[PDB]
RNA sequence: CGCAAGACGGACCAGAGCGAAAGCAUUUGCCAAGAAUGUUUUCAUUAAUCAAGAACGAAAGUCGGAGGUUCGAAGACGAUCAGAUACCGUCGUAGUUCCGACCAUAAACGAUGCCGACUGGCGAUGCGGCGGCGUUAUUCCCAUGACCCGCCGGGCAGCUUCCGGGAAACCAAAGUCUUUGGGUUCCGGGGGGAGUAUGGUUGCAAAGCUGAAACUUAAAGGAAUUGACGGAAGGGCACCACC
RNA sequence: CCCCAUGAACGAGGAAUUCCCAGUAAGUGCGGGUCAUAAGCUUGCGUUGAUUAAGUCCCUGCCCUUUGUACACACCGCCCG
RNA sequence: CAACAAAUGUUUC
């Protein structure tokens, strides 16, 4: 609980940070420095089946469990950094990344700016597993 | 075994921006209650927050970001200093279009106060309206002479003047325009920005300048 | 749908209408009588099916010319319509405005004319 | 019997070019060969912006984009109907097209 | 994280999906507030003007 | 948030460039080199193409170091299957990278020898030169510069064409071939046996070059045409199909 | 065929699978064919009369283009040690 | 929006 201050106007600010890959979805607010956390919870924990780790509905549930303690500790508002697996990995967003954002905005926290932060590399380190491609 | 939920223990500080910016009350951040076994100011002091120049100015500065680093603490107040400017991702990605030449030059330079900076610029050739080639590349000769011009300016424009004037400079984007003037004689160019600035070496301390800039 | 008129029917309708327009009508009941007079049709169901489709046509024709049907009366109507011509539109109003070169087009064509100059700027391909 | 006069995809004046890795199989195909499709999309999407516009501070703001340039090897781009077998005749058309620019009220 | 129940009224019947062809596309006027309007998939036989009871009230599908 | 290592130069990046080919995208400097163009410079046949000989030559592999980040030929694992030593997951090897030597091969494909002339339309584009009382960008006019339009070379190509070629697919070269003759070089004579045996040669090795026969057999093969059929694409249609 | 007696399994059907959209499914009797005799059959007929898609191409089957094919006794076809 | 199994086998014709 608690609150940086009474502020019948402006809102105490943190960082939202969502990593959407496929097979899961992390939501995550931290202090705008980053060094200090605040309430995490993934799209995994709120369903069982592995196959359903990453589904938007789970993602919703997670952004809901997160927004709770967010507005329960002190953050009134949050600026978001959405991400993909990145690296040489896919470079496209995972499915319950949108769902998480809709869930927290809908929840009734506050939104501020957006950038994508997936790590794109001035390319190399050879991508995994070999030349002939995953065959399948 | 149940224990120590941590927010119920944490303390709040109000992040303060340098003077050249406009409004200066960045937001708030939480640290642990200082215990002799600890310096909440310790876990507080080299923190860096990245804020959008638009929130910082108020605007057209949608793209552009400034990195603000906490340089000291005074009771619930924490005075930050310029640490960098980058662009984001969307903006940068949006300039980079096929059929045009992408030109990059960067230079590393020491300011009047010591700071060592690596400072990048960028530009793209422009088709000019009654062109009817579809593309609009530049020649190798062109880019080599254009880059020299960009580099000469960036060293010229940072050598003279301290971290603050570079800042005061990068806001109204006076470098951009200056490049545009020195380069149109050589080849078109659409876009043009100093797109990033990287702090390489910091001078020693001095609360004097920091306060001059804050306070 | 399930009732899509076949050519043997549709043809007869185009057919009669071409040679029968001023005789035929808006109403199923009467053409049906007319098909007895102006055509020899073997079964009553066919003759009905014919009368009916040709009426659907007459209903349509009498609301806008239909894609492939011509009758003497419709030809006359188009003919009269295809006369129109006003105060007339060019004028073009005192003085032609030229793009020059088109000015140099007359200038080097040995030809007097009215004038005006506004022709500059190049000029991209695509 | 030779099918495409272009063989794979456009080389002619080279004999070599670095290869890229398919964004699906993680395969490997020369960059001259390989279907490439740009992909620009809003951070937020369809429905969100309304809660995204209401929940935010800032007076408008006005949405970033994610930009990603995809590469597919032949089998992936076929598989997923990025591109589709075209008759012996249609194959010759390099061009591109659709009728409106599908951006909200398309298929 | 959540619960509510939503009343929505059919505006326009889109067509049919499911490979079996047994789910009908629908467009819904949001009943409690008309200034909303969304696409939902149906099990039963649906015709214009009758009412859905939405659980999820975001989501908004497509194929499947 | 910083830092270390090794790797690699994304987006920009193209039927676009250069290089004999193999191949070649960070900055900047040095070093010599290569084509095109311009050129009322220089020589006077210097020249075309080639047994023998020789230079270069992706990858793997091999010798010894550096190095191993990344990924990973082998192996061991988890699944899947009737079987699975596989695909699929995981751990992970030599190896990938780099230096000094080997090795001489890739559907090293444009599957198309090289050189010269001649025969056909249009518009692109890298580049050089040339021309415009065309545009825009400047100062007091400029010298600038980028463009538009045209002309000419030589690039890689494209497009459309009952010239003409070809069995056709196709091809402005695969044209100028029975009306068979511009120069030169190389390889093939049904298919298998076979790039095999054997001798020579080169190689540290792995292997490379040259290269038979006995016997076997009546088609091997090419191209186009059409169905049949597809766990290829748009496909449909029916409770002998589903719902 | 009847009359009595003896009074079975079967207390809802796995793998599978047929058929069906309106007098239709299903219950229910009758008549005709076979016929000397012999209906558990077939073959109609009226009676009583719903549930349920109202469509689509997923599986299956067959025909529509485009496409690939070493197939053409045509995939129930033609392959390696 | 992306992606997804499957063996063998008797005659002249």
Image (tube, coloured by chain):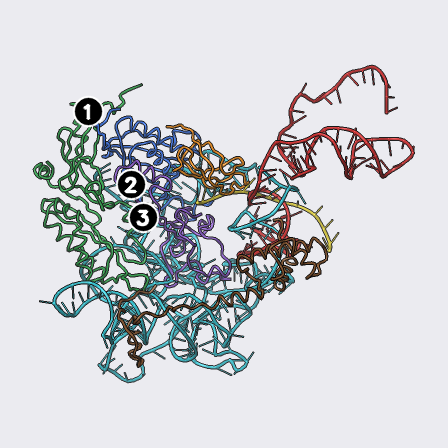
Chain colours: A blue, B green, C brown, D purple, E orange, F cyan, G red, H yellow
User: Is label 2 on the same chain as label 1?
Assistant: no
Q: Earlier in the sequence, mark 3 or mark 2?
A: 2
Viewer-nearest of discs 2 and 1: 2
Mark 2 in CB contact with mark 1 (< 8 angstroms) = no
Secondary structure at numbered mark 2 = strand
Residue B50 location, x and y as percent?
22, 39
Residue C5 disc label: none
The local crowd at label 3, few if under 14, some if 14 to 19, many if 20 or more residues have their Cα within 10 Å, is few
The residue indicated by pointer 3 is: A123
Which residue position holds label 1?
Answer: B33
Mark 3 lies on a secondary structure that is: loop
Circle 2 marks a residue in which chain? A
The residue mark sitting in front, 3 or 2, is 2
Q: Chain of mark 1?
A: B
Residue B51 horizontal/vertical position (percent): 22, 39
Mark 1, secondary structure of its residue: loop
Image quarter for residue H6?
A: top right
């Amino acid at each position: 609980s608690l609150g940086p201050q009474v502020a019948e106007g402006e809102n105490v600010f943190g960082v939202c940070h969502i990593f959407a890959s496929f097979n899961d979805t992390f939501v995550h607010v931290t202090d705008l420095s980053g060094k200090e956390t605040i309430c995490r919870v993934t799209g995994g924990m709120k369903v069982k089946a592995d196959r359903d780790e990453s589904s938007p509905y789970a993602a919703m549930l997670a952004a809901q469990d997160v927004a709770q303690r967010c507005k329960e500790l002190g953050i009134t508002a949050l600026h978001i950094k959405l991400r993909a697996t990145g690296g040489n990995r896919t470079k496209t967003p995972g499915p319950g990344a949108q769902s998480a954002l809709r869930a927290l905005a809908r929840s009734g926290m506050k939104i501020g700016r957006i950038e994508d932060v997936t790590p794109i590399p001035s390319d190399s380190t050879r991508r995994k597993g070999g030349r002939r491609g995953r065959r399948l | 075994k149940k224990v120590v939920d941590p927010f119920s223990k944490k303390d709040w500080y109000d992040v303060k921006a340098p003077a050249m910016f406009n409004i200066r009350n960045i937001g708030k951040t939480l640290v642990t209650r200082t215990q002799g076994t600890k310096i909440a100011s310790d876990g507080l002091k080299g923190r860096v927050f990245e804020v959008s120049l638009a929130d910082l100015q108020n605007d057209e500065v949608a793209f552009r970001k400034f990195k603000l680093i906490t340089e000291d603490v005074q009771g619930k107040n924490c005075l930050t200093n310029f640490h960098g400017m980058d662009l984001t991702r969307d903006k940068m990605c949006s300039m980079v279009k096929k059929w045009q030449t992408m030109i990059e030059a960067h230079v590393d330079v020491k300011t009047t106060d010591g700071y060592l900076l690596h400072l990048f610029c960028v530009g793209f050739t422009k088709k000019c309206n009654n062109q009817i080639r579809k593309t609009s590349y530049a020649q190798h000769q062109q880019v080599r002479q254009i880059r020299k011009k960009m580099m000469e300016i960036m060293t010229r424009e940072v050598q003279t003047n301290d971290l603050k004037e570079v800042v005061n400079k990068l806001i109204p984007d006076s470098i951009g325009k200056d490049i545009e003037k020195a380069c149109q004689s050589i080849y078109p160019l659409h876009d043009v920005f100093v797109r990033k600035v990287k702090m390489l070496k910091k001078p020693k301390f001095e609360l004097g300048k920091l306060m001059e800039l804050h306070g | 749908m399930g009732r899509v008129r076949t050519k043997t029917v549709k043809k007869a309708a185009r057919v009669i209408i071409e040679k029968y327009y001023t005789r035929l009508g808006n109403d199923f009941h009467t053409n049906k009588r007319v098909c007895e007079e102006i055509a020899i049709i073997p079964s009553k169901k066919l003759r009905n099916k014919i009368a009916g489709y040709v009426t659907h046509l007459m209903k349509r024709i009498q609301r806008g010319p239909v894609r492939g049907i011509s009758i003497k009366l419709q030809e006359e109507e188009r003919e009269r319509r295809d006369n129109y011509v006003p105060e007339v539109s060019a004028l073009d109003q005192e003085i032609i405005e030229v793009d020059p070169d088109t000015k140099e087009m007359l200038k080097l064509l040995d030809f007097g004319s009215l004038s005006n100059l506004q022709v500059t700027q190049p000029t991209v391909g695509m | 019997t030779k099918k495409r006069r272009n063989n794979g995809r456009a080389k002619k004046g080279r004999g070599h070019v670095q290869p890229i890795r398919c964004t699906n199989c993680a395969c490997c195909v020369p960059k001259d060969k390989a279907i490439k499709k740009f992909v620009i999309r809003n951070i937020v999407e369809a429905a969100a912006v309304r809660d995204i516009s209401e929940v935010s501070v800032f007076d408008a703001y006005v949405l970033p984009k994610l930009y990603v340039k995809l590469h597919y090897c032949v089998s992936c781009a076929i598989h997923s109907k990025v591109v589709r077998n075209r008759s012996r005749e249609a194959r010759k058309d390099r061009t591109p097209p659709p009728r409106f620019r599908p951006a909200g009220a398309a298929p | 994280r959540v619960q509510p129940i939503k009343l929505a009224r059919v505006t326009k019947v889109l067509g049919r999906t499911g490979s079996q062809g047994q789910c009908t596309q629908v467009r819904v006027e949001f009943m409690d507030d008309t200034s909303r309007s969304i696409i939902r998939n149906v099990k039963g036989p649906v015709r214009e003007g009758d009412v859905l009871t939405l659980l999820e009230s975001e989501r908004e599908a497509r194929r499947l």
